[PDB]
Amino acid sequence: AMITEKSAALYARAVEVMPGGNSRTAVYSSPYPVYVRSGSGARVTDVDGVERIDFLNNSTTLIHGHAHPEMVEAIAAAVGHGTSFGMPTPVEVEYAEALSARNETFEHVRFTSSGTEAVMMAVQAARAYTERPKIAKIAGAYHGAYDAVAVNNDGSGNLISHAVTGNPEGVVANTVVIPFNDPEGSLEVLRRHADDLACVLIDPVPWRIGLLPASKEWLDALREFCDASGAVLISDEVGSYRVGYHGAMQLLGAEADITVMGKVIAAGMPIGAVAGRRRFMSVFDPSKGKPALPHSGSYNANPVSMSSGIASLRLLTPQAHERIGQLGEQARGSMRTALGEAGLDWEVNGLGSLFRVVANSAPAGYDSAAAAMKALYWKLLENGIHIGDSGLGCISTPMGEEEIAEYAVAFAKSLGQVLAEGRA
Amino acid sequence: AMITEKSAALYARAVEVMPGGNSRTAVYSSPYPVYVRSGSGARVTDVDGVERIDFLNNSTTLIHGHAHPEMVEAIAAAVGHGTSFGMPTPVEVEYAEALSARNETFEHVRFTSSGTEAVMMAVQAARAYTERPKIAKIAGAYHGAYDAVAVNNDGSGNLISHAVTGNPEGVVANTVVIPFNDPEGSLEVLRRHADDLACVLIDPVPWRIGLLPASKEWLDALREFCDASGAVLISDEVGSYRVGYHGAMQLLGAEADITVMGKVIAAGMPIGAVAGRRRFMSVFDPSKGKPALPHSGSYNANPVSMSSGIASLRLLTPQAHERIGQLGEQARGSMRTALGEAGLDWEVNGLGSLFRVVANSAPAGYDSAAAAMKALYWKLLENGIHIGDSGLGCISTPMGEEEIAEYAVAFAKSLGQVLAEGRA
Ligand SMILES: Cc1ncc(COP(=O)(O)O)c(CN)c1O
Ligand SMILES: Cc1ncc(COP(=O)(O)O)c(CN)c1O
């Protein structure tokens, strides 16, 4: 049924000018991905003219969906006045005030052009503040391509160092890994390295290891360890911030020293942020002599990304946050009903407006649970829905109960087709 | 004479929500920087309502100046269709075709959200391709905040390792440094490390060590060393690309394996690119199983930055490139005349549309040549001109003979005022 000839023709062009026709690993699918030309509200139109409901929203960036009129007005007005300057602007100050106001711990903020850069600068800040070399991160959790965090970042629960091809021992030896939600297992590792630990980098709701939240007991163990050792507690909320109105740590009853943000804070334009207590952020301050940690960047605090940010935070009201959490609960419940009626043991995890289908047992005719989840991703595309090819999804503010009901009908139909094709 | 009350008031707000009221080290000035609200063509209007001619153009990013109508149209129209997607778009293919066409060695390209990220991914690509740990870079050259390149990066010619506070030995020991334009001094270092060198990272026209071009002899020595050792030759042209129509290495008679680009290639929207021969770029290819080097990023190849890129490259015609080169030659000549008439030993370096005033001997009443250059930066601001506080500047395509003549008058007046204040 599905016509993808214009996607295939773009892919044939792309392979001549990009490696494997790709510029972003996460958006590649075999034999080629679907190419898209426009979005409006909750819906994306592909290059073959097919409109689908988007349930992943640029990897959970687009909390307000596609081309929200209030976002478009603010961004286009900023573009007209100049895209970037070699001087600070009023909107950087306005946006830092707006972001600082979201959480007590966001005393001072610094803007980058991505979450990948913001994670990197939060780790550099902790190393400059402590003058210690090691970082600790969660086994399996993903934090972007920066080489200190591109270690054990693939969903595995093993603690043995495993890094990207070429990441030197010089980097990999200074990143230690802790088991998620295992307080005693975590403290064993952290106590072994306490004298040398600059930071403990967590994600309170890491999607790559199943989108389960950090427990109170595990957050308490790490917060007490950081207070005792002097290690900086960094919460990477680039993806998970959206689960709470004041971010993920606040929802779970905890406080970070530094929080990394991105994605929803600007809801589509390039952004990252490092926010935390004044003392940890003081490594960046250039006002009293050379800073401990220089941090430049051509697009830092550019007024287009600041204007996108002001508009996003204005639209992300407590009422919007509540209503998308209602829709997330409706979506997760409809998926669990559909998986149980189909006779699969797969789980659906998530908080607020985030979810992830976590494939467990591979059904007949699939080599792995991940292959069965890729097949479900393709069947959902045929049935008018975009989700992540390993089960991630989210709600956008343009959605109502009708979109989630349409998704539930597509989800049940798709499961049926995946299972029937595996048995053929 | 100069009124900065609205800038002071923004700074007073900024210090409460950013470290030292700053989000980008390079745009800070004591006691506070000038804040700006808008740009049009070659001119910037500050928050106190004062219009000046911009001769630095967001650190040489804005090759087409501020809010170029054709740039504004392309960007604002792209925004209306969707700022970013979790799927590739037609404009990524169109822009990769446009950029690949600029140099024979740009066979395969990948997009990032910054030059800092692009440098990082080019170093990771060479380490993945060779499976060797070390990189070599130029003593003094700046490549952004990534910790492997944030070593010997502040204008010094010393080869002794000097890194940011907290950069661990595990990083710093794998970055070796070579003296710019010294073939035998460079080959001594590179031969000592040849078995362990993944790459030689250069900038062919590094502004931080005085904006002098790489010699034919030095580029030939490095190209031959890389061919012999299997090290990847990386040219970081994030700033220097603009000196030639086919980039900096081509102008100077050389070929890189990988070229890093940014800034002018999108002329004001967040961008970076890694462009090189197919074999080096193959580490990123996801089309034949898992790639050696995963490379994602929420804003990679976003259609707003791609649309900015297509418009910028379309506007950067051979005719435009020649005209800004002529204006740069006229500007450099007018500065050298003014410095000679004022009795300073200062030099003016640069190629094409780039220049740098290189302060040598401190005149009476200044502790250092750099303090004297900072004073000239402030006097130029008073006389209606923005340049860099250490002498960097550039020409933009909106400029004509009238802007370059106005600059020459302001430059001579400002030098007189700097010298008179130092002697007073
Ligand atoms: C937890 C986390 N941290 C950082 C990043 C990287 O952010 P960006 O895509 O803005 O570079 C991501 C992206 N998946 C993320 O999930
Ligand atoms: C040579 C060079 N490389 C890379 C960068 C970083 O690029 P961006 O500002 O886009 O991160 C810079 C910026 N100063 C640079 O000058």
Image: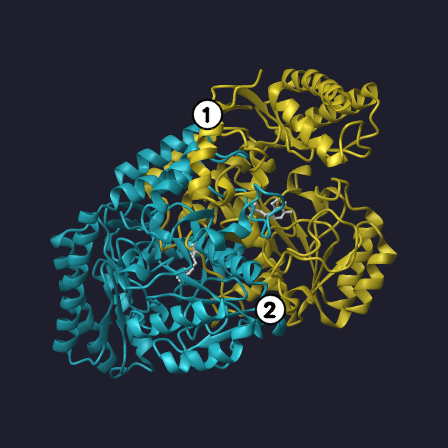
Chain colours: A yellow, B cyan
Which of the numbered marks, if any, corresponds to residue A128?
Answer: 2
Which amino acid, mark 2?
Answer: Ala
The C terminus of chain B lies in quadrant:
bottom left
The N terminus of chain B lies in quadrant:
bottom left
Chain label for disc 1: A
Report helix, strand or loop for mark 1.
helix
Q: Residues within 10 Å of mark 2 (few under 14, many from 20)?
A: many
Residue at mark 1: A6
**Residue B23 showing in the rendered view:** no
Which amino acid, mark 1?
Answer: Lys
Q: Residues within 10 Å of mark 1 (few under 14, many from 20)?
A: some
Could you say where residue B221 lies in the image, as x and y percent from the top left?
Answer: 37, 74
Left or right position of A203 against B178: right
Quadrant in the picture for residue A27: top right
Report helix, strand or loop for mark 2.
helix
Which residue shows up at 29% across the image and 46% down it? B66
Chain label for disc 2: A
Quadrant in the picture for residue A368: top right
Left or right position of A51 against B79: right
